[PDB]
Image (cartoon, rainbow over all chains, first blue to last red; front, side, top):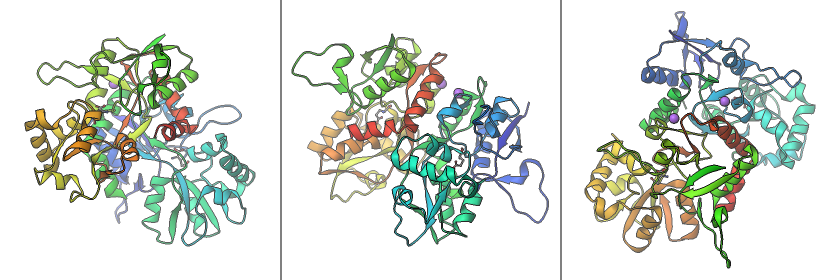
Amino acid sequence: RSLIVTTILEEPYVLFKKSDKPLYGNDRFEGYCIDLLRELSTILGFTYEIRLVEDGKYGAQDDVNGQWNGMVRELIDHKADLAVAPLAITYVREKVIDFSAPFMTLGISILYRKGTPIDSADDLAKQTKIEYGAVEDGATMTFFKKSKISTYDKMWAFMSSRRQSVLVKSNEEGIQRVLTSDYAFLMESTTIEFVTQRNCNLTQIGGLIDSKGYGVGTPMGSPYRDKITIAILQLQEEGKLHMMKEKWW
Amino acid sequence: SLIVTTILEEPYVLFKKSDKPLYGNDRFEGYCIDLLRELSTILGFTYEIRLVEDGKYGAQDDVNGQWNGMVRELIDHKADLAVAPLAITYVREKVIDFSAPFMTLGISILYRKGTPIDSADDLAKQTKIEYGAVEDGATMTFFKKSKISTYDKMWAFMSSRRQSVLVKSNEEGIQRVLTSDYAFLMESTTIEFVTQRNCNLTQIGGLIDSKGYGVGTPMGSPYRDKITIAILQLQEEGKLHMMKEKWW
Ligand SMILES: N[C@@H](CCC(=O)O)C(=O)O
Ligand SMILES: N[C@@H](CCC(=O)O)C(=O)O
Ligand code: NA
Ligand code: NA
């Protein structure tokens, strides 16, 4: 049977294809992760239906009742067979779903305007004039919430106390905030790279604060777990992942 | 106690130096040894380190398809884990399981500074400067299977001059760079260790591919997910980075 693939809108990984005429079904979507899905489909021989995650979330655990949401929850509940998205492979998620080998490596960094003295997270941490934040309840925010590093704990103290204002619903909103107020956005380096190639007044500040990968998510115990990993390694070795990144970035 | 297979390779695994005799696991040190200890602290297992009997990483004999090295030790359940700079590859993942990568790297070129050589293409288009790789490892396999004209040219050169340009270990290749006119195709992580200690050497060109090192387990291992979880925990805590800083 066809697989149900959950994903999320996020440039340039997954986007609505533009056209004068209305598109339907899988035709509606394009991007790095859609090319990835197409390549995986060819290797493994499955057909699929792409469905945007119903609640529009990546997947985090509620801090009161411990329940999962987002693409992670859709996999736990067997509402999707695969998640193919810029979904960070994390310790807490791997406890509830399985990730393939990573198809992209990245890390947290800072998006901000050019031509300022700010050169690092420490530079942000030690002031309050320039506000900073991250996507609410994503892997980036979780990094700061969990960190025992003085600088990062101080940044978490700042962000959490200003959660209503500095934590945003999406990368888009974070970028929109950088462009409209004195605001620096903590976000994933791969996505920063796409943003900065299209906004020449924006730049990455400093280097990578951590390291992680994006991987394809499957429900724990899926008969596809190892098949997907093997296919990802095939695409990696074929140089296809590199071509895909060059195409979309 | 879990049996852990590994392989000598600076600075991942090496014999510890001491004025006094050493015994058991205490004979070994290195990044992978520290990693193994960290995995044990998280997962709570005890273990015995054993160097891979045949001293090989793991490849398939092209004649009979037989595996060797640490890969074979896992397939045959002669070890419970492999903790080493073992590349996560397509052919290996079909017969054993790898964790999430604890390190990311790529093939590159180890050679001298100040030369006319600035890329793999520069090596491929000549024959005065010899070049090669570790026999039967992931790097050699990259070249063997490549459809890129530059890399297939390099494979033709290496496979014909096997006895002369392919080496048995990274240490042998590095000494070859240091003592003859030779460029060594090898993994960028290990190159960085070498260039920090040999100021006349440098990496040439960028990474030619991308891959990770992972902990290997036999398929069906009850430890597979717990190992990946622990690796991800060490990643997030910054502990893998600290270990890399320690050994490099
Ligand atoms: N890619 C992230 C969301 C964005 C972010 O946290 O920076 C995740 O998987 O949670
Ligand atoms: N680490 C490699 C061996 C060295 C190399 O091929 O450059 C492997 O896993 O096969
Ligand atoms: Na899992
Ligand atoms: Na496998």
